[PDB]
Image (cartoon, rainbow, N blue to C red; front, side):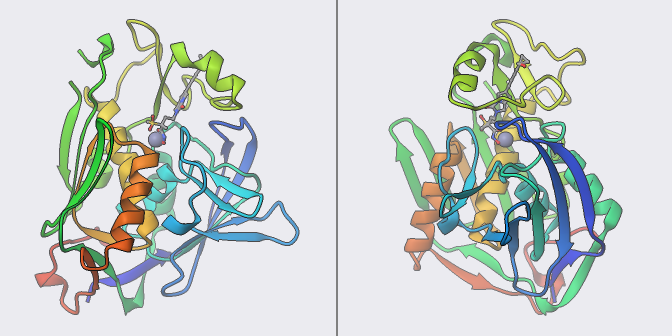
Length: 297
Ligand SMILES: C[C@@](CCN1Cc2cc(C#CC#CC3(CO)CC3)cn2C1=O)(C(=O)NO)S(C)(=O)=O
Ligand SMILES: [Zn+2]
């Protein structure tokens, strides 16, 4: 069978919040079968645990934020992307502060640290959410849709006019083991234009060339430029895999986003969950006939 996966060992990282600029200590821990990904604010007494699920999402403003009462876990999309990409069902994510560390802006450091520690297949069937009908949402021109597909595939189009794009489209099939190579190292990005305002609403406070692609009027500012020519839209795919993992299981279907962000991504999951004829939960008692395959543990 395609088995549930956790971490083989505990992982410790130290970084900064992209939006808060706060020093945070990250501890990823093994978790039992059917735990899912649970975030934990360990700086609070008592410890406050928020499962990484669609229902727990609060604001979706320049990131995906989980909320329980007045308590928040901000910027979960890149770490969840990494977990989703490597096929991690069950893990406790402890944070010493409200926001996940930004690292280099990518999921690369997360996939590196996780695979350094390694994965543990568990004695239980991995559950997948199979898309059964098309499910679309639209906020005027912006647009997000799930369509049935035999495997996992994510398509996305940046529509907006800026000199730096030399149109950014991409469409990637993650039915096999493509995630690390294709999208993992795609960094987040922001415009010099927006920084003054974002800092005024307590955002991008930890933002710099170290953890992001910074885009002036005409040029990328980063000394060493891009990792891929389509890095911008590859990151929109990275974000999408993160947000989509808030379903709490791996997807068997296709996602297409036209200028869709965290807001629409979450609207999509909320509608999908509501429409129980548009999806079902499946396991695979034989991995050889499954539409998805994963890296050796
Ligand atoms: C939400 C989104 C973008 C997130 N970011 C990344 C990001 C970097 C940035 C900056 C700066 C800077 C500066 C200087 C000041 O020190 C050095 C000049 C601001 N910003 C921002 O809002 C994302 O990746 N979410 O996961 S996205 C791709 O749009 O969906
Ligand atoms: Zn992002």
